Image: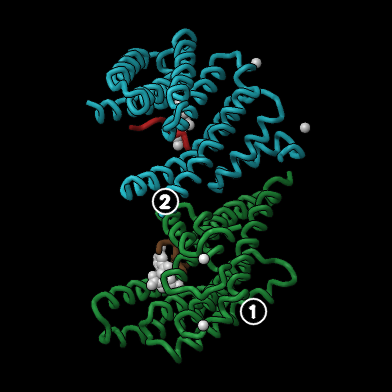
Chain colours: A cyan, B red, C green, D brown
């Protein structure tokens, strides 16, 4: 649908849509930019991720409200409307996963891009897992786990322990363990080891990098405080 | 609990 | 598009959409309910108004952000995207105005419903006027003024000066005078007279009605403080 | 300035 707009204009409009808090537009512009077929720069990857995180975040919040009302009730309207929102959410997750599979991951050869996209793949399978209840729930969970694990393996070989992408990947994989995989001890161990290894590498960083890394380390600590 | 909020570029 | 869903189910789903902060859905459900052709109850009128106020409020906020960026700039992208948002906003206003014209106003015979719908008509022409720049800007402004004036005339004959609909109508008509019609003195006079006449009628009210009326009176006072 | 906020039923 964005095929007639220049790549650079789609990127410019995605930035304007972010300023205007028009995240559905932002996601459509960034989908159009991906579909031009060129690899994404670091800033463009961040625009893609922010756009879809906001879209799916609103859907997840609505699904949780409706799911809570439905569980309290147990006419067809609450279930029907929860199902409508759930289908829309699944459609957005499938769209993101489709962009990653056609063809962002296969062309991503640098550690920073490949880890970023595999973390995204884990995240969007995780959002699918949050609403899954059928015969594929196990397979959806395994798909999230596999994507996160490949990203972790690359990040540990190629990035320092303070790298913000590495830290955010570990944070989200720990949330996967706690919330999806019923593995709270694995979640706590991963968050603790990630935090401690980052702490020991802070001395290597500039003031600005220190700020970036310590911000995410505080999120790991916040989860550890809630989980212990 | 909290994943990366991820909602501001 | 909602023609196959029961009226009562549309209303139930509009209430669920409000809880889930899904205001576009809420507006679509309430449009479907209006298009069943029956008059709306007081609560249903409020659901219709809340849904569209939230939809158009997001559009207006985005339009203001983009308009500010465009004015600072003076490629085509900022103007093109501001125009896209503006067209979408105009489409929502035209949809609301169309519901009022087909056929909510013509069937509204009680003062509470007729004033409510004429206030809405003034509000949505006012939102059109905020973005108007062409040869119909004067006519759009006059359409807002005419709707508000008919609502005011009914409200002064049929409602007490503390009635919340009457108060909110006067508040919004004063904003029209200040922001759209370049008539700040008329805005201030209307807000002051409305506040003073409501104050003198508070003694007639129950505790709960007093709370409802004084809340809107404080909004009139807040505007008077900003304008003087 | 402020019209009726109008965004919560
Ligand atoms: C996945 C990820 C890892 C690390 C960062 N980071 O901030 O360095 C981000 O960035 C974001 O997208 C973000 C983080 C926190 C809050 C918000 Cl609104 C965005 C992502
Ligand atoms: C047009 C109007 C007049 C009076 C009231 N009222 O609150 O009594 C309302 O109600 C609303 O829709 C509303 C008012 C304030 C804040 C919010 Cl979120 C909604 C409308
Ligand atoms: Ca080109
Ligand atoms: Ca029926
Ligand atoms: Cl490559
Ligand atoms: Cl009637």
From the viewer's perspective, is A60 left or right of A187? right
| CA neighbours of label 2 inside 10 A, class few (<14), some (14 to 19), many (20+) | some
Residue C26 locus on image (x, y percent): 49, 57
Residue C149 locus on image (x, y percent): 55, 84
**Tag 2 secondary structure:** helix
Disc 1 C-beta below 8 A from ligand 2: no
- Give the letter of the chain under mark 1: C
Quarter of the image where the N terminus of chain C is located: bottom right
| CA neighbours of label 1 inside 10 A, class few (<14), some (14 to 19), many (20+) | some
From the viewer's perspective, is C37 left or right of A200? right
CA gap between label 2 and label 1 equals 43 Å
Residue A136 locus on image (x, y percent): 47, 26
User: Residue sitting at 53 percent across and 59 percent down?
Assistant: C5
**Tag 1 secondary structure:** helix
Nearer-the-camera pick, C27 or A79: A79
Q: Is residue B9 above or below residue A193?
A: below
User: Residue sitting at 73 percent across and 67 percent down?
Assistant: C134
Q: Residue furthest top?
A: A157
Quarter of the image where the C terminus of chain C is located: bottom left
User: Residue sitting at 46 percent across and 10 percent down?
Assistant: A153
* Residue C56 numbered tag: none
Q: Which residue is mark 1?
A: C142
Find residue C107 and report its image quarter.
bottom right
Question: Do pointers 2 and 1 mark residues of a single chain?
Answer: no
- Give the letter of the chain under mark 2: A
* Residue A78 numbered tag: 2
Nearer-the-camera pick, C143 or D9: D9
Q: Are marks 2 and 1 in contact (CB under 8 Å)?
A: no
Find residue C216 and report its image quarter.
bottom left
Residue A207 visible, this angle: no
């Amino acid at each position: 649908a964005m095929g007639s707009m220049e790549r650079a204009s789609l990127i410019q409009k995605a930035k304007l849509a972010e300023q205007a808090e028009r995240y559905e537009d932002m996601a459509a512009f960034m989908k159009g930019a991906v579909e031009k077929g060129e690899e994404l720069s670091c800033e463009e990857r961040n625009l893609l991720s922010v756009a879809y995180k906001n879209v799916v975040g609103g859907q997840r919040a609505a699904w949780r409200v409706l799911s809570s009302i439905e569980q309290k009730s147990n006419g067809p309207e609450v279930r029907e409307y929860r199902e409508k929102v759930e289908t829309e959410l699944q459609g957005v997750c499938d769209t993101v996963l489709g962009l990653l599979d056609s063809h962002l991951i296969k062309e991503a050869g640098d550690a920073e891009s490949r880890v970023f996209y595999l973390k995204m793949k884990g995240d969007y399978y995780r959002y699918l897992a949050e609403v899954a209840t059928g015969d594929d729930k196990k397979r959806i969970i395994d798909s999230a786990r596999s994507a996160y694990q490949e990203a972790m393996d690359i990040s540990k070989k190629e990035m320092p322990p303070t790298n913000p992408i590495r830290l955010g990947l570990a944070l989200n994989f720990s949330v996967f363990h706690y919330e999806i995989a019923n593995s709270p001890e694995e979640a706590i161990s991963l968050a603790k080891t990630t935090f401690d290894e980052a702490m020991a590498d802070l001395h290597t960083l500039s003031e600005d990098s220190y700020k970036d890394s310590t911000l995410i380390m505080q999120l790991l600590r916040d989860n550890l405080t809630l989980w212990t | 609990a909290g994943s990366i909020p991820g909602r501001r570029s």
